Length: 31
Length: 32
Length: 32
Image 1 (cartoon, rainbow over the protein chains, first blue to last red):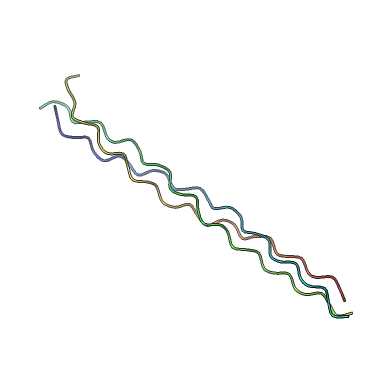
Image 2: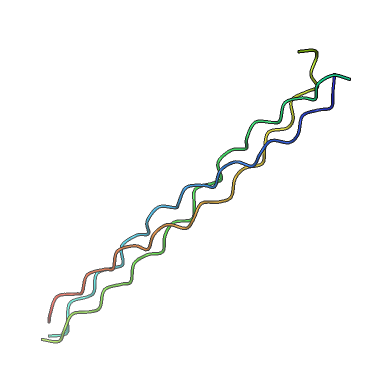
């Protein structure tokens, strides 16, 4: 039999990360 | 002598990306 | 198709995914 086969091709790029958390609400205005 | 082995299987997909950044905190309310 | 050599090693993992999209802006606070 021949030589061991070549190393496999790299895998595909990962999926995008999840969308970030919402920013905090602003505090009520001064009276 | 004879055929070489098959290529290895394709690699695994890469890890999921990092979480997106938080949105900006909202401005405080207008004065009363 | 005569004895083949051993199958190669599995490929390396792919690159990390992109960072996620930015989060939604927080709402403005109520007026005082």
